[PDB]
Amino acid sequence: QRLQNQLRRLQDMERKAKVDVTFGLEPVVLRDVRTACTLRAQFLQNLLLPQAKRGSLPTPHDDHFGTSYQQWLSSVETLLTNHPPGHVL
Amino acid sequence: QGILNAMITKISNELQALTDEVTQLMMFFRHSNLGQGTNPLVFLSQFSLE
Amino acid sequence: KGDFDLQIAKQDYYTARQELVLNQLIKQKASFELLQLSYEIELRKHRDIY
Amino acid sequence: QLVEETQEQVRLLIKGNSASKTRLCRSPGEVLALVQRKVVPTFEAVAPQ
Image (cartoon, rainbow over all chains, first blue to last red):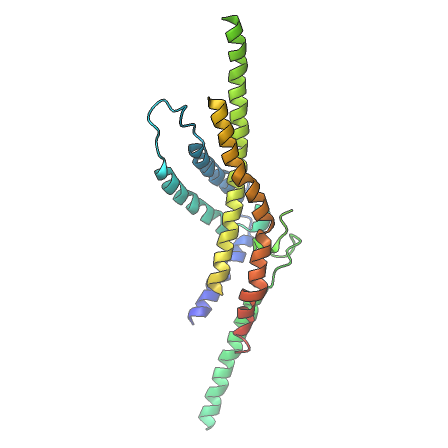
């Protein structure tokens, strides 16, 4: 019974991948990829913010290592759950 | 023995249902040939990224 | 003042365009990291269902 | 100083950028190797059991 419920749970990943969920038309996959890439771009920009160019004291952005990564993980979870890898490609 | 055979028939129906669920779940993971958009886009590793 | 101002007017352009190239590399790295993370999540799903 | 530090930054970017394309070329391969040899054998194995 538990694995039948597991089958019921796992028979919706590809089903939700089948539908082209679309929010402005631009799908939610493209907007979610752009938003997640914007968050990861902020992460890499904080990685590549020039330390010597910083007028103030250097800020070790490990909070940006963690919390921005968790927000990115939530956005990527929504992106992967609602969308197929083919139109991701 | 008659009730035993009826309940073995019940459990055989359960085993056929289990095999039905297994066969239902095979096609998602035997889906390795995603060289087209026509086939359900299940896993990314079944594609070609070139 | 003129000799410094010509090179500085070029140097602001150099800084802006090199930061544009840097942001292009950053966006490409973000997309590649997203795609690799999706592959890793698919692998974890495969192992868990296994 | 910003230009030379950004050259170091470009090296620190390209060290992952060059590896990402190579590991994503083989990203289908190792997952499908796990599929056809470990996961899908267990996927069948429930039914003959």
